[PDB]
Each structure stands twice: as C-alpha cells, then as structure tokens.
Length: 16
Length: 478
Ligand SMILES: Nc1ncnc2c1ncn2[C@@H]1O[C@H](CSCC[C@H](N)C(=O)O)[C@@H](O)[C@H]1O
Image (cartoon, rainbow over all chains, first blue to last red; front, side):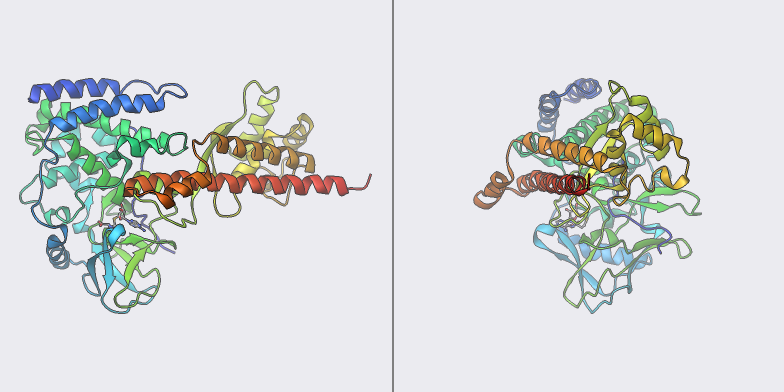
C-alpha cells in the first residue's frame, strides 16, 4: 500500500 | 567550575565504558552511575536554553511557519489533552482515508540537514556522529535550539521541555521495575546516555572542529537528556531525496499526533516530496485526531516513547532461549535451526494477543525437544516447505510426544519467570487501586503488571496445549 510507511518514534539502536 | 565538570565527566565516561557486569549486578551498577550523573546534574543549571512563557503560546507561530513552507494547517488545531499532552483536534469532519496532513521535506530535521548545519565540521570528523544517525539528530536539535535564528526555531520552541522516558525517572520509580524483563533495557538506556554525554562533553570542549559550535559555551547533561528523549520519542525513518536509501528525521506538525490502535496511515510521497497522513478513522469536528505509531510493545512505548499504552494489542514480553552446548544433540539441533533460519540462541517474544508464541518460537521449541531420531529424519528430508514453513505451523507437529515436551517446557518456563517477579498480579492491582502515584510510577507499575499478565496467559495456553496432546495420545487406540 504505502511505498514508504512512516513509523512515529521508530525504535533505533542507541548503543554506540 | 568548568574544570571540575571536565573531571567529573572523564570519570563518568570511564565508568560507563566498563563491560556489562554479571547476572544480578545490573541494579547496583545503575545506582553507581546515577550517583555520578546526579552529582554532575545538580552542579549545572538545567537546560542551557529555555523559553519564557507557556508551551501553547508558541503553537500559532508553528502553524504560521508550517503554512508558509507548504504544510497543511487547515482542518485541525493544537489542543491540550490532559495526560496525553498536546495533540491535534479536528475543526471539521474528517473522513477515514482522507488526506488531511502533509509536511514538505524542507520543514524536516534530518541527518542531511544536520550535515549542512553548524554541526557539519564536527560531524565529518566524529566517528560516533557518522555512525549513529539518531545521535546526530540529537545534536542537530541541540545546535539549532541554541541558535538565535535557526530556521526550525518555531518547531523547537513548541517541543516539550521534559519527557517521561526512564531517563527522567527517580531512583525509586525505576526500583518498581526490579526483576522485570524491561528494566534491563532501562539500564542500557541510562548507561548509553551517560556515556554519550561524557564522551561528547569532552569532544565539544576540546575538538577543534567543535570550536564554532553553540554548545562549547554551555552543554549540560539535561541538554543531552532532553535531546535524545526528543529524538527517541519523535524520530522517523524516511527515504532520501532520490529514494535510494533511508534516513532518520524529525517531522514537525505531524509529530503532534498522539497514538491509538490501528494501522500506519502515514507514508512519504517521494513524487511530491512530502510526508502524507490520511485519516486513520472518521474524526468528527471537535474530536482528537489520532494515528497509529507502530506495532511496538509497551516496554518500547515506556522506554523509547515515554508512555504506557493501555490495551496495546501488540504488547509482548521478551524471553531468551537457546540450545546448550552441553546438549549431546547440540550439533544436530543447531543444523536444523540453521536450515530454518533461526539462531541457536536468541530472544523471542511471548505475545498478549493469541497466539502467545510465533511460528519462529514454535519452530525453535519443536527442534529443542526433538529426539535424535526426529532430528535425523528431519535433516534427511529436503522439501523446501519443510525448512521452516511447516515447522512453525501449529497444525503440523513433529509428533504428539514432541508437542507434550515443548508445551511442558514452555509452561514451566513461563511459570518460572512469574515466580521471579517481586510482586504478584493482584499486589500490583492493589497498588494501582489504593495508592496515589506519579505519572512515571504508574507507567512502571502498569508495565510490570502487563509483563505478568502476558506470562500468565502463556502459562495457561501452554498448559491447555499440553493437556490436549496428552489427551490425543491417551485416546489413541493401543
Ligand atoms: N496514547 C497516548 N497516551 C499517553 N501519551 C501519549 C499517547 N500518544 C502519544 N503520547 C505522548 O505523545 C508523545 C509523542 S509526540 C505527540 C505529541 C505530544 N503529545 C506533545 O505534546 O508534544 C509521547 O512521547 C507521549 O508522551
């Protein structure tokens, strides 16, 4: 459906 | 004393760069780190930049700025919604699937605009900034916040001044989460944030490519806690301008929408170069407009979004399972799992919504409980459908014996996890019912209660499946 769905506040890795 | 802060942050950097401590050492390490972070924080004067007046006073300027740069400002207005914070309220009836909100790329704060900003020189030299797009976005936000005439000033001045991510929890609010699964990710967040603050405070104060940063003057722990919390609660993945890759971004105006259950109805329109949001449902005039953020767990909503979402249909709890190398059948089980695409040891989830276990977990449990003969027969087969597709399907057991073994294991393991919690389900409900609790305390107690409700559902589901396959074996004629 959506070619580029946007997840609000998508979880990312913060372990540098 | 700037030289004292530099010495305290050097000490903080070293502490938060130690290896992970063993089992049962995590809480005391967190307390060790909180002690030093708080001593630094109480020696500093909060956020380096503050805005006089009320948060709502700045929303008109946000709407005007958004409108002048091509965004939608018609049909909704910014309103305070009590414990959900501010949000959008429809001014007129909005039909489901109607396009009502759009935000051109020029309004966004991205890793790309970070690169072309005053942070650019330091970005090109710092290894962490180049690797961590979310950290780069946090410093982009801090740099523009400290800039008097930033293009994004109308957006930054309407952002919250604090959040309910666990970074803001008091010690005893985190203590409510002792013996939960979620607390380990809380520990990690605190240690990561403290390490990053100490590292970058040293860099900003010493690196020559940071000499012109607006943060060399003032850069407090509260600044960095605010920046990373802003990013983790609001950041998004979007395609790059050509669409060949993806990037992280803050999306003004649209990110004022609060969350409800549903499906994602926001997507990037590359042809018109703008984010676009269609109505998740019919919203009548005067009703709050909600979107669906994503299929995240309540641990993720608490830790990364700073709220607990009641009746989260996607809620789940993490469980770690693996084959032991002490298992005399380790090699065969590892080979079957590899064929299935499953690691020998990994983190699975137990789900609130039926079924409590995914196809991946069911497949793992079946292989873990296979006899030597079942493993040999499985490896001898070569139908592509049998690598994983049937192996994870409830209606295609290896054997009724295998089912009884795996459900017995899962029942016992979920029961074991329940026994390790410091409180029971009804003790939690009594706290929530009879105690006056802060917002953050309620989030913590609801979170630990939710974990146990999922585990008890898994216990009962494993038990009824164990009983069912035991019955099928008993009813089989001799
Ligand atoms: N269903 C919900 N219940 C409680 N808080 C919610 C919520 N949905 C979103 N939020 C809040 O909104 C934040 C995401 S940004 C959404 C706008 C925000 N309410 C604001 O005033 O700026 C989250 O971090 C959380 O604090």
